[PDB]
Length: 164
Ligand SMILES: Nc1cccc(-c2cnco2)c1
Image 1 (cartoon, rainbow, N blue to C red):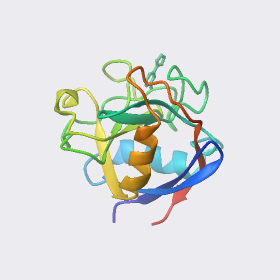
Image 2: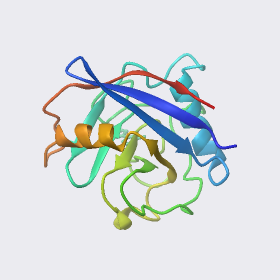
Image 3: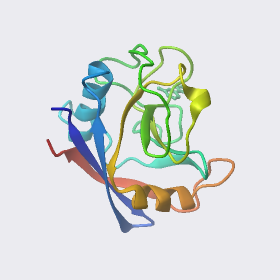
Image 4: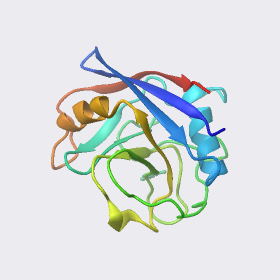
């Protein structure tokens, strides 16, 4: 079946708990595979130790810049960037997992978890999964955001990997 992966998240060095994500490899296999491998770290790099660097309440929590930790970096398991696989899955509500980008076909490792329906991102960002468990953790992360995206606590993915 589709991969299940996890992110364990700290805020200022204290654990918030675990976010479990289903990756929709049935719809976006290349995008799912990238995220899965970045969670396990099996290519020699990935999300472990990186941060949620941009969090905006009533919008989304963004992470995955494990090279620059500020929204300018990250890389995929294929190369620095890879194409938009498809836009078949939509930003239907809170819990949607989607790829951040810098325009068409600039997927790397940065991703976001929506805390609302973000319908205006349909056809622009590749949705590739959703939150199975840990929306409470996502809401905590969200609460440490701001209008500018600047976080008020240091939000770190302390551990991550594959459950199935
Ligand atoms: N992959 C990805 C996602 C979001 C932003 C960027 C980005 C920005 N400046 C250089 O790269 C890259």
